[PDB]
Length: 123
Image (cartoon, one colour):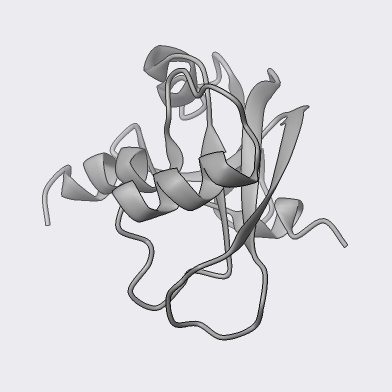
């Protein structure tokens, strides 16, 4: 209930220095982060350092966006893992897509607590 939404944000969407950002990378980090009981169908990780991600909450590196979101001014190395196979039960098979662009998050008390996945559900 307190700042735990932010640490959960880090757990779900942050990875400081991934290695290869290939399929195997996805399948492994998605398991290690526990987004595998029902297999999450899409999930994106942001790379780089925490300070600049947090700064998306201030005008320093963010802009108000849509209803209540914030869009970053800078771009981030990012990797999106998409479930492949339909069945939502393990084994969870992921296809990885590395990318570089700004992100949309929701802030709370000056901290990111939500990553908007729609801009990566790139069709």
